[PDB]
Image (cartoon, coloured by chain):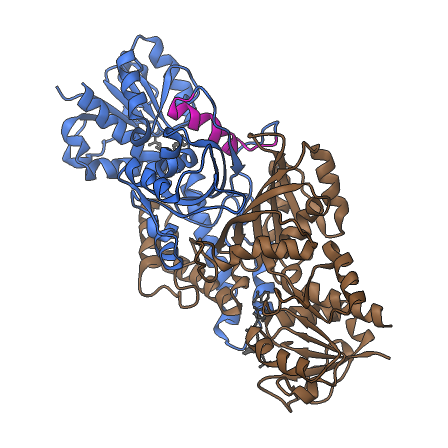
Chain colours: A brown, B blue
Amino acid sequence: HHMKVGLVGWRGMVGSVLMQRMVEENDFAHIEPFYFSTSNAGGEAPSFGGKTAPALMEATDITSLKQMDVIITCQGGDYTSEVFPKLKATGWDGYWIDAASTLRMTDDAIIVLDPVNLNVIKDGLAKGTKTFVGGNCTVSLMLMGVGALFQNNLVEWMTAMTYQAASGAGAQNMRELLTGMGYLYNNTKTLLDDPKSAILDIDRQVAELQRGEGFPSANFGVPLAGSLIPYIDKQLESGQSKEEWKGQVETNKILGNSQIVPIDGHCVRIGAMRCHSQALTIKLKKDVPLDEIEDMIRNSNQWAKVVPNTREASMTDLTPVAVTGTLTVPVGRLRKLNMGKEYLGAFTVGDQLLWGAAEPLRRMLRILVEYKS
Amino acid sequence: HHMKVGLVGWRGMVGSVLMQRMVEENDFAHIEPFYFSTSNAGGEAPSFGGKTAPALMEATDITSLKQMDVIITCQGGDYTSEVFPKLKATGWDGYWIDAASTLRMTDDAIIVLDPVNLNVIKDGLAKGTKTFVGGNCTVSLMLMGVGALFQNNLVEWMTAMTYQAASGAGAQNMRELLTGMGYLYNNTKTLLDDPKSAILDIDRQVAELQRGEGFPSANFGVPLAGSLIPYIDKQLESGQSKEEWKGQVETNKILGNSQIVPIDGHCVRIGAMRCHSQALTIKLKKDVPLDEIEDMIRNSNQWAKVVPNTREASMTDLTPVAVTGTLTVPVGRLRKLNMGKEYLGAFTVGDQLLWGAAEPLRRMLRILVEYK
Ligand SMILES: NC(=O)c1ccc[n+]([C@@H]2O[C@H](COP(=O)([O-])OP(=O)(O)OC[C@H]3O[C@@H](n4cnc5c(N)ncnc54)[C@H](OP(=O)(O)O)[C@@H]3O)[C@@H](O)[C@H]2O)c1
Ligand SMILES: NC(=O)c1ccc[n+]([C@@H]2O[C@H](COP(=O)([O-])OP(=O)(O)OC[C@H]3O[C@@H](n4cnc5c(N)ncnc54)[C@H](OP(=O)(O)O)[C@@H]3O)[C@@H](O)[C@H]2O)c1
């Protein structure tokens, strides 16, 4: 018996990464897929991975959803907020796998990142937990890299200064970033094409372009191309942004910690497509040798990598260009810092759409399939 | 009388910012300027500020240099290494003001950031110091923002994760960054113009372009447009980069600390033109109320500015777009961090060519004209 799996939000950005990865892993050999839609119910459904499906079903139709053993949705928080309470109200016994943050902090939900917390997931399955949610991209990517330090309870606290890509804000924000790159270059091309032009003239024109009415910044509100934005998501009364607030609460929930490990920092948007990078100050509980720290990271999971702390390796392997569209999570610049042997610096890069979004969800689906077979 | 000032490296990027600032401040009105060249000796000299000067003099000719009361050079470390020892050996009694890092860590030299260490500069001038050197751009910009915390002896240590602009590497690096932005957009433009294009197609195309032979990365070595580079300058034995190593030694020399305050972090290059930003974890020696920390920053100098910790103000005032080409050094996101009330987070942005390069040098020159 293959589980009946309902796919919602398969068409969007996160959903399309999920579909691609499910095809790459032949995930459809092990399930019976049913495709749902909020806009095209009745239309022809995709045939990813060589499996046909009936016509698109209404994503908001509770009776249709109750037919599934598993719902995996990349549709969004507004969808989950409407549909999830109605579906659970029917007594529906199935599993809900969600990319949206809506249910992340509810008592009945487990945040999934199985290379780090498989034990939490399996303990939850045995307890009857039915709802499984991806974590925030910044937390998931950081834990894929240095989570072994937390699992071994070596971390007293951590600050994280991030370099976040436009993909976290959405497909249209990525397109805006690229369009702004073109706006800056194409309107300074006549100066740039002349070797004898003055750099200060080129620079003056770029600043005028960034500051002018013509710059395309509808989605970010301010320019990103050629700049950065040191604020992501809503303002909290504490002065934290909501993006920054997720660090401590989601990290400690993924790990199952009862004693909270403090995590804080600044989440800053930069002009990258879909890789988040993070500069970490990690206070350790003892003077752990650097080679043992590297071994713990290397051995923690398949995807974490240690980049040797050299100029050449850092430039080639520890960048968004090295990582984008891969599942690799490099950790580099690993060094004890000047203020003491217990201060560990680390710099890590991860793809936001994979480990930061779609990949923990398809891996949770395979865990379920194996669990229920 | 009006001192005779020899200007070296006035033609380069830092020199050009310096000349513009001197014209803007009418600095040439109180000096007699003389222009030197490494490539165009004998040619007609510029006339910034409406002041004429004789033909361009040879920048490596010690006999010409000795006639100057001041030498202010933006030419580079290779220049300073060659010329400065030979000039001092002749007994030259003049002042040497330098953008290059060559002399920063010599005992006889003072690192100038007068809104922070004017007292160090005045004491050195009276003690006979004749060599004054601008600090590393990251250190100077950080101190212009949060230097008052150090002057009040409140900092136990600090980590600084930086977001450094292309200007720190050079004019050609800035041009390469813009050219790469155009390369990514123009070769993805057909996809971008179609609303129905799949974002994963657009994204696959950008990554291929960044990774291919056609991407222009001759100067940085790897792409910067749409990326970052977490390594700046030479690799040290400790694993620190030379850029990162500068933080602790330069900060403590600028301040005059005999007790070194530890400073460390990661220096990272991003795709900005000429503003450096820094995300700071500051461990304080005691629990200082946040509003008093703000007042320390406001009171420290007229260019530091406290940006209220709001989404709207951070987005519009605490960015390279807000700061570029100006003398403003905003400090924002000021907040006590989750690991305790002695932990202060801060985010600052500063123009790397002004306070990070040219501005401390022209202010030091005005200090000399006022002093003598
Ligand atoms: N964006 C991220 O990087 C990211 C990361 C982690 C988690 N998440 C969460 O994942 C959820 C979805 O994010 P997303 O960025 O993937 O959303 P999205 O691209 O905006 O897609 C969401 C839905 O919008 C509809 N849609 C409208 N026009 C579309 C078009 N031209 N192409 C494709 N779909 C279109 C589709 O629904 P129909 O097919 O029913 O019409 C699609 O499933 C949100 O809860 C978000 O918070 C996002
Ligand atoms: N780059 C920075 O952002 C920065 C920041 C702080 C400190 N500094 C220091 O300042 C020094 C110079 O930096 P820079 O970036 O200003 O150097 P630069 O633009 O390369 O200029 C240095 C010299 O190169 C010569 N040159 C060759 N081709 C040139 C051209 N097309 N246009 C203009 N000059 C040209 C000029 O000397 P001639 O007139 O004699 O031919 C010029 O004065 C170095 O010591 C550097 O470490 C730089």
* Residue A359: percent from left, percent from top: 69, 63
Relative to B73, is A151 above or below? below
Q: In what quadrant does ligand 1 lie?
A: bottom right
> Residue A79 versus residue B176: which sits nearer the camera?
A79
State whether the magenta stretch is mostly helix, strand or loop.
Answer: helix
Q: Is residue B207 left or right of B183 when viewed as pictured?
A: right
Relative to B283, is B255 above or below? above
Relative to A354, is A373 above or below? below
The quadrant of the rendering that contains the N terminus of chain B is top left
The quadrant of the rendering that contains the C terminus of chain B is top left
> Residue B45 versus residue A317: which sits nearer the camera?
A317
Which image quarter: residue A333?
top right
- Residue drawn at x 62%, y 63% as measured from the top left: A353
* Residue A129: percent from left, percent from top: 74, 69
Q: Is residue A155 left or right of A269 when viewed as pictured?
A: right
Residue B303: in sight, yes or no? Answer: yes
- Residue drawn at x 51%, y 61% as measured from the top left: A166
* Residue B349: percent from left, percent from top: 39, 45
Magenta segment range? B239-257
Q: Most extreme residue toward the left, as rendered?
A: B1
Q: Is residue B262 magenta?
A: no
- Residue drawn at x 47%, y 27% as measured from the top left: B261
* Residue A45: percent from left, percent from top: 68, 85
Residue A329: in sight, yes or no? Answer: no
Which image quarter: residue A251?
bottom right
Q: Most extreme residue toward the bottom, as rendered?
A: A42
> Residue A7 versus residue B191: which sits nearer the camera?
A7
Which image quarter: residue B339?
top right
Q: What number of labels is visible? A: 0
Q: Is residue B243 magenta?
A: yes
